[PDB]
Length: 49
Length: 49
Figure 1 (cartoon, chains in turn cyan, purple):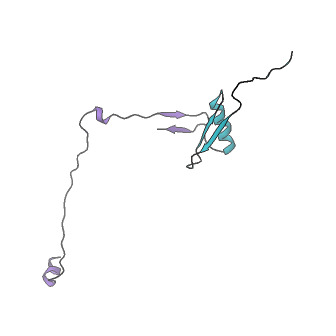
Figure 2: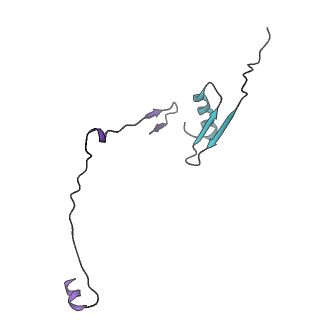
Figure 3: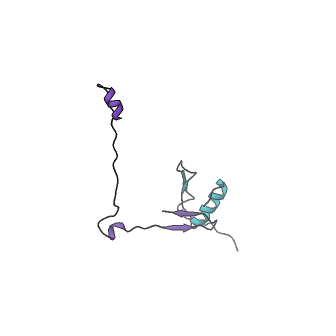
């Protein structure tokens, strides 16, 4: 049995905006799992959640 | 200051002392109500507002 592309009509898309205070980031992203986005971004920046 | 003012015609000193009772409170119980929202993320960090 062959695979299959998700083929959501909206491609992968995000905007990451640093606030400029206390290394606060806001992440606007087309995802199904915000808490996971928060984790991997915080980890990558070595920041608390 | 009394000594000074007896010896100086064009320059005078003065002293004063005032007391304070400053009451605190608003008109009703409802005016003093207050609220907060606290999250604890899975890394243990806290967000409060």
